[PDB]
Amino acid sequence: YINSENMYSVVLQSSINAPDKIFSIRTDVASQPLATTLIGEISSYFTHWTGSLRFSFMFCGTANTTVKLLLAYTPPGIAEPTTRKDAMLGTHVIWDVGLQSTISMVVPWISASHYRNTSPGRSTSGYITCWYQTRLVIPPQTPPTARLLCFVSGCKDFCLRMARDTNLHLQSGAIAQ
Amino acid sequence: RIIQITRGDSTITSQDVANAIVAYGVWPHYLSSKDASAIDKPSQPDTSSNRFYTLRSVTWSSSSKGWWWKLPDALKDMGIFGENMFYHYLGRSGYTIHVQCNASKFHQGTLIVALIPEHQIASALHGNVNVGYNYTHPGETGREVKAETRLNPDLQPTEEYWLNFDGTLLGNITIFPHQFINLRSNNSATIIAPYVNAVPMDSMRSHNNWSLVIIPICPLETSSAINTIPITISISPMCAEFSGARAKRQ
Amino acid sequence: RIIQITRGDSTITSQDVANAIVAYGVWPHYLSSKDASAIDKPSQPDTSSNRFYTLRSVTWSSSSKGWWWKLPDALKDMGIFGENMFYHYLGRSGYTIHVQCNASKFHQGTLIVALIPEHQIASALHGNVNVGYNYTHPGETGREVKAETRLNPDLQPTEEYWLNFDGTLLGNITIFPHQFINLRSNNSATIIAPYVNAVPMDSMRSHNNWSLVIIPICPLETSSAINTIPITISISPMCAEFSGARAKRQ
Amino acid sequence: RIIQITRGDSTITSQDVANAIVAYGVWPHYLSSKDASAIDKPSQPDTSSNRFYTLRSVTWSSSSKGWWWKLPDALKDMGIFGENMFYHYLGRSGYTIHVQCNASKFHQGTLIVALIPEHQIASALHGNVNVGYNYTHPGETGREVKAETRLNPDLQPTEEYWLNFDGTLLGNITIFPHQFINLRSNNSATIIAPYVNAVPMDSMRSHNNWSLVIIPICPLETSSAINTIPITISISPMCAEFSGARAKRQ
Amino acid sequence: ALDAAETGHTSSVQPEDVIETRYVQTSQTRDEMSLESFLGRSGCIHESKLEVTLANYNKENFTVWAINLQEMAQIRRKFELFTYTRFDSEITLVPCISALSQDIGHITMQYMYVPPGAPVPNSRDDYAWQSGTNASVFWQHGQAYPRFSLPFLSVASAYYMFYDGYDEQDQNYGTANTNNMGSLCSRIVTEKHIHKVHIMTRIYHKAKHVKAWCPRPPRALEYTRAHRTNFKIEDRSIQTAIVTRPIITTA
């Protein structure tokens, strides 16, 4: 998917009676892939960060189609979850996919320190994790498929310190002209 | 016909639901100094347990017959709620319950959901028998209703759903606080209840002070290849309280 | 979620759209005596050109890759707007844009539309090369993105849509004023912008002071035999002005 | 020289003790809105955990060398305190501590008790080594000091008590809040402390934000056949708080 | 908590909506995040390397460089973040002498800002080293680092970070049209002498009293061609800052 739009997107399988994991990610602002977001790059230009992050999600599938889904966050010091019920013990939202397009939700700031370092080395901030709260149900002869697109931004809570020449980009040699 | 719900840390919605009737109109509340029996200032986990928790997926078909749970036992494993229950001789709590049951515009069928009191289940077998603890207290695993071969049958409850498993007629079951999942009417259904007992608080693990029933009053169907839909239920305890702290109950 | 739109003589609607964000909140306006460079009282065609005009049908498929335009060049043929542009050395205008993209309830896929500034396109080829005028100025004919064999490739722009054709990541493109055509969310999408430049007005044909991009972020599909849908875009110029009248530009 | 003590549900006394100095005179308290980092309203188990809990019996002899603990780890198993700790990424708590150490009128010897901060223990072995988690976090089992054969020695802390296990002189240890069990002076000793860190709250299981040391400064003896006495310590957490609820920590 | 991201507007804004928070004095200043901070730290811009030629000392020993922010990546990426920007400029010179000989002696060095249509010096002896009105400035061995404040220059309100067209007869597409600032220049001022030496000036700038115009997405890949946004490098492939993983269910 990398050389294309599709790395911004995930595909869902209406065929599956299961509770199971759809995807998961870190939450450290300058970790992959999040670093590549513009908040990611701005954080990558910085050494300290603070405050909670906004996350948002559109059910990009066929308008006739229904589901409800679990979006969840893992407070760290612990492995990334392996059952839906694990994520249900974490802070989470269940998406009523009503007429409205998007669910939006926040990883709460739960750093011990008022800031955290923007890039972890041997360190962690926690996980995003995503699960089939119901099965996805298309009505008959709809495409046997759906799409989801995922967004992030700084909340009103968000801030940075120690502006530094960013990790994210490299120059080799002379820039020609 | 839209709602959002928020308890302790966690939130719920349907955008195709008609609001819960509050059971008997009594919005949930803590015990009163006027009515209490227990002497201590009791355990208020508040937000950390008057929050939602949800059961494993059941799923249903035209062939399916029914499901139910008994509370608090159905929630014995709900972290804070579960252990705070098991570590006290007594407690009390009401509940907010929502059942999740969306289909397409192209399905038919209907479930009745009934919140129900002590719901004292009848045996399967005739004669000098009564229900065994393992089955009255199925935990979150619950009791789906099935056609066959449940062992220890002498201690099993009856499977007879249209006799409400106690020898009372279904359809009069609307005497309790209830709703219908009707796939045309709604995509979900909801009910909320205070605490209740003949006693101001109760021996949680020893007595299911509330119970919840869901019944396929009208058979599930669609022409679509998705011949079946899951159901799941989420519950938050309400004003949850516990008293007589000691070791973890076995 | 319904709108109607009226500019100069012509009107537009969607009854399944969420309103435009106005670009940076600045509702379009004429130049100011406080900021101007040009000396004359400039040409205000008003209603006769601050009115809608629309582009030839593009159409899209699961296999499709993207489309864009550069303004005012994309409107060089829009009668009054087009010639009033070509007959002046300078002008300025904002725009109201709506993209028309209805599907059935039974389709999925999504486009991002981004209004975008100078959007300085990168070459296709490596090395000591730059984009040729014919391609930077595609007129109303625009630039759809294709897999193959565009001649004069050394002077062609890159086709690399997910690198925004300039070596910047897509998905951060929401930095600009933007909308999604999402077939569930809406049947159309809209954006409006004032004039902008580092200069109070600009050499219209020599510099595309604004640009517009539409990208298949999620592939078009339906099970229906109508495997593809057109898109079309309509634009009205805003507060359009022109100065330094002389012959028609070639 | 008599005291009684009451926290959360449980009570303590000595009728031969001189009162605790409160550490730095700061009586324990919750976090402030002025100083906090964490965003939620945090977990206040209050009475159900700001109550006493006590460690397994150590016992001592003229031959004995010392004992210590690191907190909160030393209390990881204290029911409500322990799990509420393990289920949160962060928390904070101060402590009230009393050490129980009665002898007859016919015994001599003395212990120093020191509450101590981060107390960053030195390795046993020389060179490129550091202390392993199993030993920094001995749990309630604690670290008694012994003459011999502790395995994994490269990851063991030093046994060198009179060098405070960190290369600092004992006897200056009275720089910290401290008391003496002196068998003539008292039959017990006590200390209380607020929370402390460079941070407004901390990663409980990952960092022992406080530590407690007891040392046989003067050898135990009596002529009586009861050649040895147990010691035990009881602790209540103070103003205990927890934030960032998730699964149980391993 | 529900919205239409398709609006273009940012999503459901508020953190207190889905967390039962305690009140906190969230009280961390955004001032380091200010533009007069982020733009307003200096960085290097260009590299004026020269050799002192002997055989015609009088001819060769000068350099000229076309002023741009487009050939050192970090500074470039600060400005490759907007449509336009405006600022006054701290300019700072880090002259360095490298010896190819047993000594350097005293050395003195000229710089000149050559605005366009100044006569460009052709020779280390050119009359153009006279500078009645051009900003020309001097450095010598043992002197402190030279600096000057240069005000915002453009004929327009702000510098084009990008441009979408041409000079009016249709070549040089983009900033190579708009960004004709002319050039910096340098030249050894000491007369012919025996020491073979290299002079290198690292030149630095910080934008302050800054203003900026409509943010635009950051550069994803190595630079290539100063004015031009070209990025598809020769005999190479588009290895962006994104890194792949084995499965999307594994963090």
Image (spheres, coloured by chain):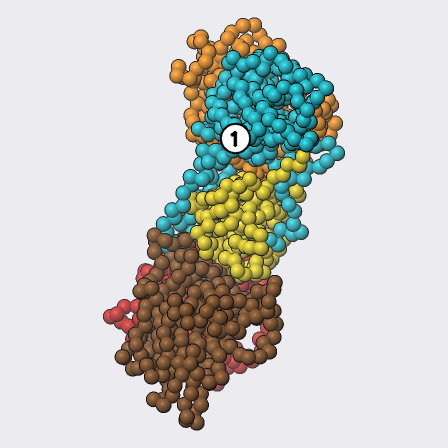
Chain colours: A yellow, B red, C orange, D brown, E cyan
Q: Is B24 or D30 nearer to us in this picture?
A: D30
Q: Position of residue D77 (x, y in %)?
A: 47, 73
Q: Residue at x 60, y 78 (%)?
A: D149
A51 shown above or below A170: below
Which quarter of the image is occupied by the C terminus of chain A? top right
Give the x, y percent position of residue B121: 46, 75
- Residue at image location 24% in from the left, 70% down from the top: B34
Is disc 1 placed on a helix, strand or loop? Answer: loop
Q: Residue reaching furthest top?
A: C247
What's the residue at 64%, 29% (across, down)? E104
Residue B1: % across, % down = 41, 48
Which three-letter amino acid code belongs to the residue tagged 1?
A: Ala
Q: Quarter holding the N terminus of chain A?
A: top right
x, y (%) of residue D160? 51, 73
Query: Could you tell whether A30 is left or right of B37 in the image?
Result: right
Which residue is located at x 52 percent, y 30 percent? E144
How would you rate the neighbour count of disc 1 (Cα within 10 Å): few for under 14, some for 14-19, many for 20 or more?
few
Using the image as rendered, state which of residue E35 and residue A78 is in the foreground: E35
Q: Which residue is mark 1?
A: E144
- The answer, for residue E159, to whether it is visible in the render is yes
